[PDB]
Amino acid sequence: GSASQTVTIPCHHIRLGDILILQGRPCQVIRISTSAATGQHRYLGVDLFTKQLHEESSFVSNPAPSVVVQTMLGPVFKQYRVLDMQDGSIVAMTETGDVKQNLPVIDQSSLWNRLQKAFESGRGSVRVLVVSDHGREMAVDMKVVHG
Amino acid sequence: GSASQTVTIPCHHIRLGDILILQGRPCQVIRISTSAATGQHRYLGVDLFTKQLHEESSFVSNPAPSVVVQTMLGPVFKQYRVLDMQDGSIVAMTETGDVKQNLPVIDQSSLWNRLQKAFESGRGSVRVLVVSDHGREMAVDMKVVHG
Image (tube, rainbow over the protein chains, first blue to last red):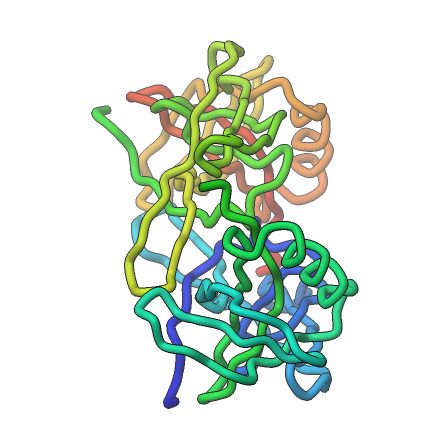
C-alpha cells in the first residue's frame, strides 16, 4: 500500500469528531480553532492507529472570482462484509470476494460490542467501514444494510 | 442567471442547519431521516427565498469496489465586500469591482444586526456570503477578513 484515496471536505462541514487526514494520518478531530493572522482553520486530531496528536491548518483556494474556499482532506471509507469475529479481530470480505482474515477493530465508542450484537442477529446485513493507512487496514465504524 | 455552481458533500458531513440544494432550491436542513427500504438519507429543508418546505433523498454511488458513498449537493458561496447598508439592503462589491446596489439580507439569526455592528467598527474587513438562485442573489452570512 502506497497512499490512499481522499475526498475534499469544505471546512464549514467539519465538526468535532469527524475523521480527517492530518499530515498524512487518519485522525479524529478534537479541537477546531482559527488563525488570527491568516484566517485558516487549525485542526487538532488523534491518530487512529498510533493515538498520537497531530495538527494541520486548512488550504485556502481562489478558484473563481469572489469565490474563496477552505478545505481539508478526508479518507475514503471502504465497506467490507463480516464473515465472523474472533477475539478483537474479524474475518472480512471485500465486494470482489477478497478475504481478509485478521482485520482489527478500533477501540472507540465500544464498537466491538455494538458489532457483536448486530452480527448475532443478522450476519448478512452487517458491514464494517474500513480505513487504510499505508497498507494497514482497520475497522472504525459499522453499518447495517437494509437489503 | 441560468443554474449555479455546486459542491458535492458526503452525507456523513451534513448536520441540522447546513444549507443544501434541495430540488434545485437553496434550503436550510431541519430534518434528517433514513429510508428503511433503500438506506438513502432523506433531507427536509426550508427554501431560503420562498420559505417553502422541500424534501430530497441522497444519491448513492459505487465508484470503486467496496466503496459506497452517499452525497447531496451544496451551493457555492460567493464573497462580496460591503460598501454600505441602507434599510435592509446593502451596496456590495465583487472581487472584480462589479457593484451591486440593492443586495438583500436574509432575516435569519439576526444577521442584519451582527452585520451592522461589524460594519461600524471595520468597514473594510467585513464580507457577506452570497447565495445565487437563478439570477437572484441574497446575503446569508457574514465574515470578517483578518488582513
